[PDB]
Length: 82
Length: 82
Image (tube, rainbow over all chains, first blue to last red):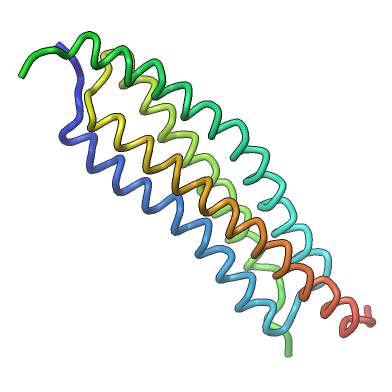
């Protein structure tokens, strides 16, 4: 049968929150750290996070949109029951 | 003194990795889950992740750029010592 979403929904929620919050959390570190300001260490840290998150936003946004595209359609084509 | 980056660098690395990899990890779930395809549960899950990550990319990208802007300049203005 379909390994659907019930228990996995929690993992989805828990990780959704963890992923987004941890990213922002780390930015919170950077500001709380910028209270004293580090050299290239700080610069490199957030710069990597920034170039990575943006690079990844592009790949993941397109991925996500397409992944759900095929899933959304695929699911509502196959799931026609209650 | 400055609460600088040495031990915090590891937390930065560990969390940078955890944040980005967990987001992609969760996409991996979605595809491994789309192998069977869930209804609105799947749709809602990734759609939220997508709208959130993009909303947040915008806020965090601008934040990060400005946070390091002030930190980069501020730090290299203050840190002129070895």
